[PDB]
Image: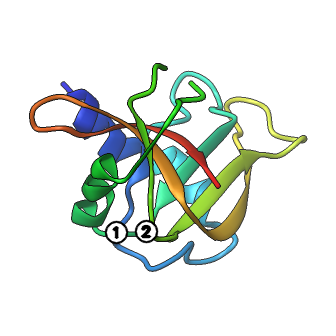
Amino acid sequence: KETAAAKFERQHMDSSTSAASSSNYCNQMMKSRNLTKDRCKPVNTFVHESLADVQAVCSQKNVACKXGQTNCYQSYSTMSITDCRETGSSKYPNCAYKTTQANKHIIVACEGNPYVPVHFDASV
């Protein structure tokens, strides 16, 4: 099973590279992170930072969630992220994605005790 925190890690964390490794990154990672099992998920962001740096965002700038409520927080620093967005010719089960590297402030939803990231809301 996956707690909300654990699912966030699966869907959104990849501390093992400093940035998308190549233009094939999302094509590989959307599959490997189990985001294409039952459908092609259209959009998903990965964060190339330590989990400790991402966790601290839950104490940074409080903002309204895009979806949630107002349990979202925007990072003071920018972070290395990858935007994965389904391409027009994609069709399940052949899910294909544009990989875009970015360096943006992230916005996460946080919950629990301990109070940790559970959703990737947005970037700015």
Q: In the picture, which quadrant includes the C terminus?
A: bottom right
Nearer to the camera, 30 or 67: 67
Q: CA distance from mark 1 to mark 2?
A: 5 Å
Crowding near the residue tagged with mark 2, few <14, some 14–19, many ≥20 C-alpha atoms within 10 Å: many
Q: For residue 48, which numbered disc appears in the image?
A: 2
| Residue 16 x %, y % | 34, 73
116 vs 102, left or right, is: left
Specify the quadrant that holds the N terminus: top left
> Is tag 1's residue or tag 2's residue first in the polypeptide sequence?
1
| Residue at the limit of the structure toward the right, as seen here | 88
- Residue furthest left in the image: 113
The residue located at (56%, 24%) in the rendering is 67
Tell me where residue 10 sits by quadrant: top left
Residue 15, disc: 1
| Residue lying at 55% horizontally and 57% vertically, measured from the top left | 28
Image coordinates of residue 71 in percent, x first then y, are 38, 30
Q: Secondary structure at mark 2?
A: loop
Frontmost residue, 116 versus 95: 116
Question: Is residue 33 visible to the viewer in this orientation of the structure?
Answer: no
Tell me if residue 96 comes above or below residue 64 in the rendering. below
At mark 1, the secondary structure is loop
Crowd class of label 1 (few under 14; some 14 to 19; many from 20; radius 10 Å) = some
Residue located 62% across and 24% down the image: 39
Q: What amino acid does circle 1 point to?
A: Ser
Amino acid at pointer 2: His
Is the Cβ of the residue at disc 1 closer than 8 Å to that at disc 2? yes
In the rendered view, would you say 94 is above or below 65? below
- Comparing 81 with 90, the one in front is 81
